[PDB]
Length: 148
Image 1 (cartoon, rainbow, N blue to C red):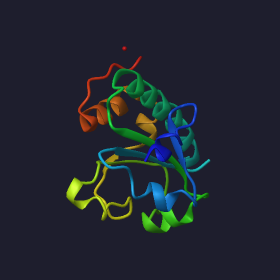
Image 2: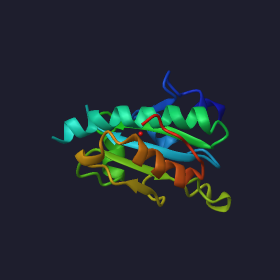
Image 3: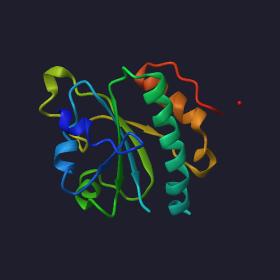
Image 4: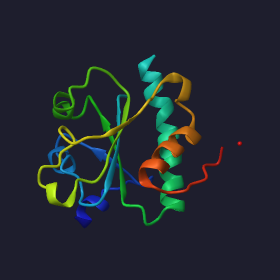
């Protein structure tokens, strides 16, 4: 699965495409999947939380290097299957898939697997603290985001 890990762009975030979706949606054993479902005003919300998302991703990579998490970003306009699969009616969404239970790995997929969803609204679009706290609790890590 070193393949998937090496998909991390310069910011440590993995772009879901219509191609790698079937693969990525099956996740990585033991890895949390943090998935930002976006589209580039809901467009403004999408763009705003992008920065927050990356900020916290960076914080987590930096301060929780051991954490088994993968940050994904998906543009709903690039992978329509994800849209159908996740029954998406709008954007953005930030969902977090816990790793599948070892015994239920094969049945893991973003579309059927339970997930935490971060309440993403304009009021917290730029709140790295709240989002960091959200991931921190899920990832069971203690992080300090520069934000007061």
